[PDB]
Amino acid sequence: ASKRALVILAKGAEEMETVIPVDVMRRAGIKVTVAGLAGKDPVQCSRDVVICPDASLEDAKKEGPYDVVVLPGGNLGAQNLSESAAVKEILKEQENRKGLIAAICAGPTALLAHEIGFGSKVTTHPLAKDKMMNGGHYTYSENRVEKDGLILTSRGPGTSFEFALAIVEALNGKEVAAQVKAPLVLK
Amino acid sequence: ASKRALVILAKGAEEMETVIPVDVMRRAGIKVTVAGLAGKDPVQCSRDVVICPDASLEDAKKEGPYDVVVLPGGNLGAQNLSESAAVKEILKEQENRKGLIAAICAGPTALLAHEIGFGSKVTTHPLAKDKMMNGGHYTYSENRVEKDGLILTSRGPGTSFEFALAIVEALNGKEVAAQVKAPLVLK
Ligand SMILES: *[C@@]1(=O)C(=O)[N]C2=[C][C]=C(F)[C]=C21
Ligand SMILES: *[C@@]1(=O)C(=O)[N]C2=[C][C]=C(F)[C]=C21
Ligand SMILES: [Cl-]
Ligand SMILES: [Cl-]
Figure 1 (cartoon, rainbow over the protein chains, first blue to last red):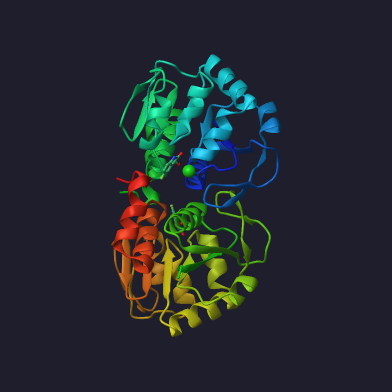
Figure 2: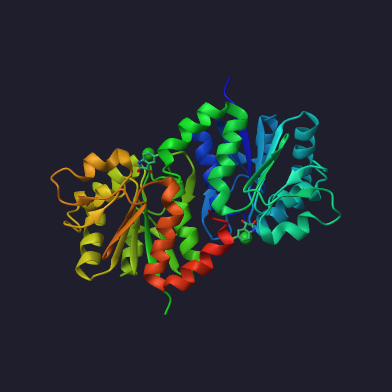
């Protein structure tokens, strides 16, 4: 059976961090749902790219659970994710069922806000480190991608391919990730 | 005065190759217009990401000329660009005025279709090489980014940051490109 990914898309999301994982996971045969935090309407990303979500988060949640829940970064996107009671519920449920949670750039700060995965080794964008580390509830890493069990984090737009391929490897295995990677012309 | 970029967005465009240059150029202070080939309506990219263009191409052309015209790849996107008389007119005008033209992945095959920049050194996605080289009207390169004068080409999703940063360097200089690059966490 095909794996299923939920990508939570908030106003101010970093569009590169949103699109690269969506595209790469689709390349891997994953069924991806781009879910609008605010509802069904188009979303103005951080650099003004406008993306039309597949569904509202409200609707997508009804089709859960998912093999991965993906949180893009962007400071303002991550803040909106961190402030959301709906996101809290989704992540809590995912963690409780031992499902993968993947977050990039400022995205991992929503894990802090929602008390997810405390004790995990994590990375973030360098500028989000102090926020993520407030309280010392995680151990910090400078690895471009960090996978500690079912908490998978990464650093920025420039680590988005690596992040996406790590998700693919976690869900579909090393060989599928390598097959997906080759046509992309990555260094 | 701020530089201005026209990004031509067709059905079947590769969304990563569209979003990465838009975002990165905006980070560089470039005024970017995401112009819908087909009109003003949202565009279904190659991996089903839906992007809402800033304007129709018809409308954006009225606000020309631009310091760069950018052609994303995606096989089907590039085919739509190659078949467009409106694209032909834009590229011909750009070339005639010694304005930069930038194309990635299968995107450079639209330069062939529209007889642009013959004699230039170019690259493409490896799978688009034979198409681009039909007639021997260009010289082929395996460089991740190739800039031959005012024709700037690149290879794939995984070269999109390098492509975008080369555009930024061409328009705004080396120091701006380096400043834009650092926060991205590129390898
Ligand atoms: C990232 O997307 C984010 O969440 N925070 C941040 C800062 C700088 C940057 F270049 C990207 C990002
Ligand atoms: C690219 O975006 C395109 O235009 N052609 C092609 C083939 C394979 C790939 F992975 C990307 C692209
Ligand atoms: Cl941001
Ligand atoms: Cl394609």
